[PDB]
Image 1: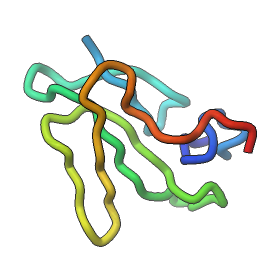
Image 2: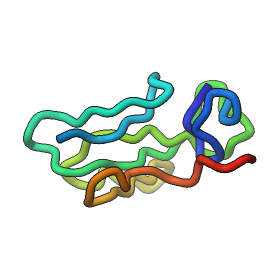
Image 3: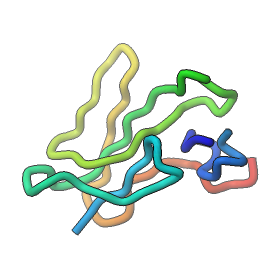
Length: 14
Length: 74
């Protein structure tokens, strides 16, 4: 769950 | 009017009262600092808040165009 620089979804980002 | 966010929201949309004029990109990491490279905490700005020893804080000057790379299967 995060908005890193590789995803926006809290499933792909974290 | 409004801006984008990223912070404790999954995502959200606010800007600050009339003083700020655009939206920004705070690059850092989580306390978990996960294997995703850089956390980016988007929000309201009047000038581009950039630092040098860690904080990249670039901008976008028009509507919706605030963010970074994110929405890809990776």
